[PDB]
Length: 87
Length: 50
Length: 120
Image 1 (cartoon, rainbow over the protein chains, first blue to last red):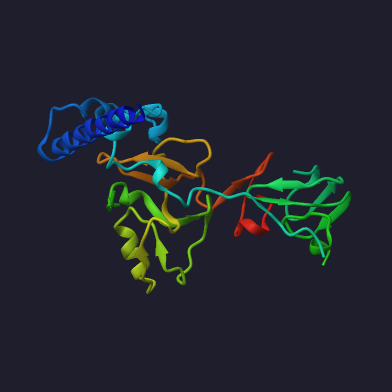
Image 2 (image 1 turned 30 degrees about the vertical axis):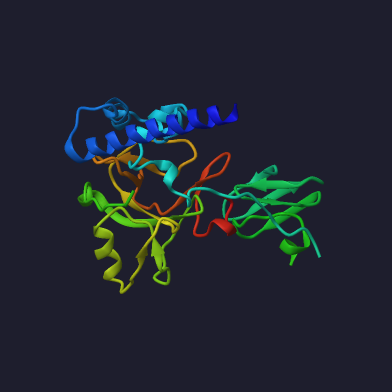
């Protein structure tokens, strides 16, 4: 029962990896391919973050792997800190 | 942020019995009035009083 | 992804500023690591005798520019511009020459030298 679902998840992951490999081959040799639309739309878009552009969709994020984004900067964060209370 | 009545080189502030917080730093202060000769951040406590 | 160096808008830059913890601050020669996207910053820092190592876990370098470049994103200081290669850039626009790093009070804008000891 659970084994069938695990195998389905493995096959879906393998298909996603195949699409990622196709995107890598595109970035290396061109290329008119599956991942052209997402990257072409994202390059001209004003969305500095991939979360708002892809809306959390897995294939869109997979096609966009390897490109610079605002989310890659950890120094822009600011952890809220409570100062010492008293003596 | 607390209420203020003068801004610039010299500042006067008023506080209540509640904690105030700013960008990345929250602090606890008591009610009162403080006067500073410089535009530095001011709150009513022993640390700033010293 | 590996950061790259770009030289666009080099003639419009007066100086450089560092962003640490989401707040812009002045640069000192004692600092040892930065995140950089510009090549002229190497000449800017070498003339003062400084050396550094590039890493993503270090304060970003931003250039003070006299030209309105990029667009404003809420929560981020200055302006953000994206290069033709996809890399992003940061700049500090100004209206008047006597501008260092400016922070926002709820009512007015006041310059500061240190965020921890200012009305910011």
